[PDB]
Image (cartoon, coloured by chain):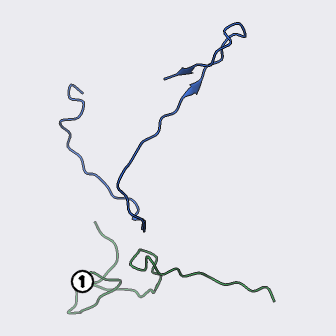
Chain colours: A blue, B green
Amino acid sequence: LVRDLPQGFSALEPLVDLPIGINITRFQTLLALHRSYLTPGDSSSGWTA
Amino acid sequence: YRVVVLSFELLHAPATVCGPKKSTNLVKNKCVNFNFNGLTGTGVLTESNK
């Protein structure tokens, strides 16, 4: 709706609790790069985001 | 002899894997006390409603 995040009337839900017995101090996320099929004359590698 | 051995890691014993399991019919409209599974409370008999 007109607001992208600062409002909403719902209820968040826990799913599954998991034990992790190791110190955690830094985090990083992933991203998927789609392979782009290029012509043989390009002779280069590209990805579409 | 086709040996099979479980694991029971027990490092996450406080979980939702308990399986005691029982069954007994309940009839309401009487002065009764009873308790199953667990929530530390007593109620009235008969299963399912709202």
Q: Is residue A36 left or right of residue B9?
A: right
Query: Which residue appears at 20% of the width and 39% of the height?
Result: A8
Q: Quadrant of residue A41?
A: top right
Where is residue B28? Give x, y as percent. Answer: 27, 84
Q: Is residue B42 above or below residue A4?
A: below
Q: Quadrant of residue A33?
A: top right
Q: Which chain is mark 1 on?
A: B
Where is residue B24? Give x, y as percent. Answer: 41, 88
The quarter of the rendered structure image containing the N terminus of chain B is: bottom right
Of residue A18 and residue A2, the one placed in the foreground of this image is A18
Query: Which residue appears at 32% of the width and 80% of the height?
Result: B46
Of residue B2 and residue A39, the one placed in the foreground of this image is A39
Of residue B31 and residue A38, the one placed in the foreground of this image is A38
Q: Is residue A10 above or below residue B46?
A: above
Query: Which residue appears at 35% of the width and 83% of the height?
Result: B37
Q: Is residue A11 above or below residue B32?
A: above
Q: Is residue A27 above or below residue B40?
A: above
Residue designated by label 1: B44
The quarter of the rendered structure image containing the C terminus of chain B is: bottom left
Q: How many marks?
A: 1
Give the farthest residue toward the top.
A41
Where is residue B22? Give x, y as percent. Answer: 45, 87
Query: Which residue appears at 24% of the width and 85% of the height?
Result: B40
Which amino acid type corresponds to the residue marked 1 in the rendered image?
Val
Q: Is residue A26 left or right of residue B43?
A: right
**For the residue labelled by badge 1, is the local secondary structure a helix, a strand or a loop?**
loop
Q: Is residue B14 left or right of residue B41?
A: right
Mark 1, Cα crowd under 10 Å, few <14 / some 14-19 / many 20+, is: some
